[PDB]
Amino acid sequence: MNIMLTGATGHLGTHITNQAIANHIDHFHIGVRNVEKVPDDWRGKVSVRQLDYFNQESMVEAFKGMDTVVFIPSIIHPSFKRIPEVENLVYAAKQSGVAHIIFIGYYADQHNNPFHMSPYFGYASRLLSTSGIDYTYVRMAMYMDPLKPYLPELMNMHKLIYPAGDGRINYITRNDIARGVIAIIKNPDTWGKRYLLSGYSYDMKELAAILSEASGTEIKYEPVSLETFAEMYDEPKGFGALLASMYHAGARGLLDQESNDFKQLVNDQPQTLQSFLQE
Amino acid sequence: MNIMLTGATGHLGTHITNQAIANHIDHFHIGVRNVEKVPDDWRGKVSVRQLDYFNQESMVEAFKGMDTVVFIPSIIHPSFKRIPEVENLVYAAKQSGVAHIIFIGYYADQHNNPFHMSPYFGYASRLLSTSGIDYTYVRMAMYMDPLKPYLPELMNMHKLIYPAGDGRINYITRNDIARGVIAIIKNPDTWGKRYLLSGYSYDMKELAAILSEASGTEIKYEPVSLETFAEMYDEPKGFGALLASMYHAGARGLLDQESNDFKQLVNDQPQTLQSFLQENILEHHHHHH
Ligand SMILES: [Mg+2]
Ligand SMILES: [Mg+2]
């Protein structure tokens, strides 16, 4: 069974690829926009194919002979600019006879979720449904990973300023999301179902406490306005409002989502934020 | 408070506009692609502006001075081709200062709904949410109206062929959808909420029985394959599979959706299919002199 992982060199893709190599998964292929940008450590361990998300032809060719495609959305924004990649995914899958698609989606996708990328995720799930192709839709919670590099700034401000009100947000590490996806890949009896890979939920007060003990510095939750947040983090342009909208969704309580899918798939509990930061 | 209804000359739009005129709604404007298709009786009762959904500046211009926009989606397909519609709606609403948007969406919009236009409706709802503009999302069930002009063919085959399996599909007249929309427009206290305008759910067996006693001819439910249905109704190109996907969603039980919103909004019961067809004696293919 030929597996094709797109966006393999991105953050999540790197975790999935390294785990697939470590587990010696057979017939594993990766797609990258420019083949020269493949880690030397992967050379000879995985099959490489050129694949550009915004070049329909490249995806049609990259999918030839593939049985299962694991698709990782890009970071392009806003939703209108990202939509073409999912259109290309479905077009290429149909053209090249792909039998199964594992789509990695984000959990901020409700009909009333204000996160700027929610339209893309709502559209993707539905487009897959209309395609007639078997698909496993894996929704993931918010990445824990970004918190580590953010510590320096947090310790400096001595304040957690996410405009998330009193909402509870569920977090999970990329490593764990990857463990779930690999488990799905290895067991076809899990295909065709909808999953939510969640870790643990924390309100911002509890988050600040976890960050405080981890950094040994005192960090208190003192949220700034949505406008102030967007304005001080608007880089690149338009990113500010988008990031703010994500926490705004949390304030509305739309990010307090949990399931035991991780445990049922990996037969283990997700790594806690304390363990992650301590690591 | 200036109200603007887009796509006013369409089937549903005509119902809404005539009802708005009957209810004496003032400050009522309409946005149409072809002003020459506007009924003469509408002259002096509503203000007419020309609009092209797929031309951003056309939408921006049409929305200048408007406070509430009631948007009726086009029939363009597939989803990727219709999307620009909602993008322009939001862009123009912001640019021209529209304070509220009443969006008329279709109920075949769940995350797992196979209907070809589900991506568009899922995208539209979410885009409105991300816009920051106040809005009222009105979802409608399946139109009963198309059944009348279709009877002739059904009578000929003596069979209802919708590939909907044993699923139940909720139906409602355009007249009733319009009454619900008008009720919302007239009372701003109903704004900002999500509504479902439903009528009655019928499995295909009951639908056939209704059409049979209404037509006077025997019509049994003998559904054809999804491929066959798309083939005998593929006009324009692509529409065939789209129509089939709609009934396929019904086969999965995704179209049996009901709510009490119509009754709570209009303070009345929706019109049944039997009543709708009984509106006028059906034209028989034979003479009765
Ligand atoms: Mg590159
Ligand atoms: Mg299959």
Image (cartoon, coloured by chain):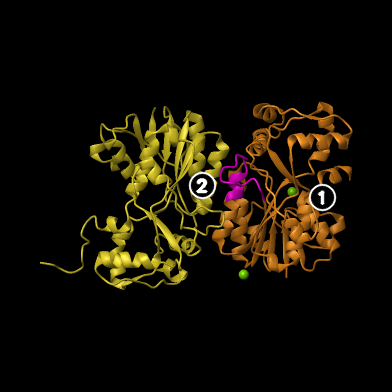
Chain colours: A orange, B yellow
Q: Quadrant of the C terminus of chain B?
A: bottom left
Q: Which residues are magenta?
A: A106-122
Q: Quadrant of the N terminus of chain B?
A: top left
Marks 2 and 1 sit apart, C-alpha to C-alpha, by 40 Å
Q: Secondary structure at mark 1?
A: loop
Of the two numbered discs 2 and 1 in the rendering, the one whose residue sits closer to the viewer = 1
User: Disc 2: which chain?
Assistant: B
Q: Is residue A235 above or below residue A271?
A: above
Relative horizontal placement of residue B280, taking residue A137 as reference (left or right): left
Where residue B278 sits, quadrant-wise, is bottom left
Which mark, by number, is residue B83? 2
Residue at label 1?
A271
Residue ID at (74%, 30%): A161
Which is nearer the eye, A66 or B215? B215
Picture coordinates of residue B154, whole percent (x, y): 31, 68
Relative horizontal placement of residue A156, taking residue B76 as reference (left or right): right
Residue ID at (87%, 37%): A214
Question: How many numbered discs, if any?
Answer: 2
Quadrant where ligand 2 appears: bottom right
Which is nearer the eye, A181 or B58? A181
- The residue carrying pointer 1 sits among few (fewer than 14), some (14 to 19) or many (20 or more) residues within 10 Å by Cα, namely some
